[PDB]
Length: 12
Image (cartoon, rainbow, N blue to C red):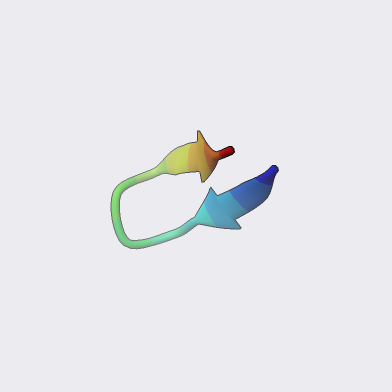
């Protein structure tokens, strides 16, 4: 996973 500061969620 990576954090997405633009939306406020984790990506997988």
